[PDB]
Length: 146
Length: 146
Image (cartoon, rainbow over all chains, first blue to last red; front, top):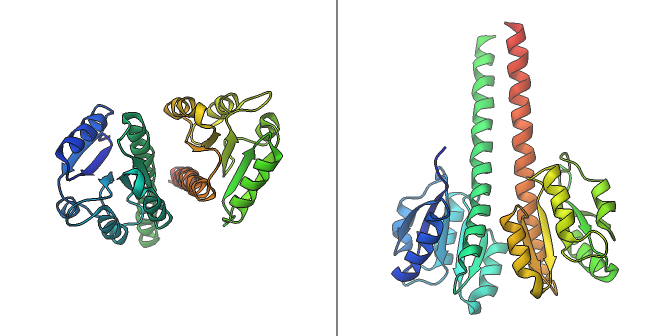
């Protein structure tokens, strides 16, 4: 089915671009944004992809965005791109539900591996949800029938 | 249901112990081994847990163990504990199907986060497999019935 999906957020257009190309060259369909609120407006518990964001941003930072996403769906994985100094915070965020972090300057291969792992997680989640809905629907039809 | 499960492999009994206690204190049930072949003898596609192993070991190393596991079940996640010098290889192994790596000397929190992510992945996989089997079984019964 559809190629793996990513909502990518970064105030820095040059880094946003380099990361977006890395992901697209890895087979992902990417929607990128300069701001978190804009990305957020397109997100819901039905989103089949993952979110990748710089942890620091003017306005809504990466952890503020993470908390909005956690509220939307704890199983929608979020990856934090972080400078060395903010790693401890990113590790704390992971303890709180964030999915993973990538250190800057970003290594293209690490970015791809982290995104692929997160996307497999989201895919399993959506498939699980789908199978459960199918089991319920079937069960409901039969229930009525008999 | 059952607590998250781990097969932990390390030739070094002191590191094996410190890692095992970290995991058990994090809620995992751990079976630890000094050698890869011994751990391997207890593994199959039905294993509900994850594998964590030092990448270097006398006899069968961590990548040799990884290749046996890949052959058993690509979705049984394997985490490599690695020294700084072997990180590039561990990254290559991840590109080839290994799940993740942890750098030595191990940080207790990073070990726990990596194990929890891998264990959630395995749990989703086993649940997916279970739901599919349930859908097939139901479908088969109905097929016969009608």
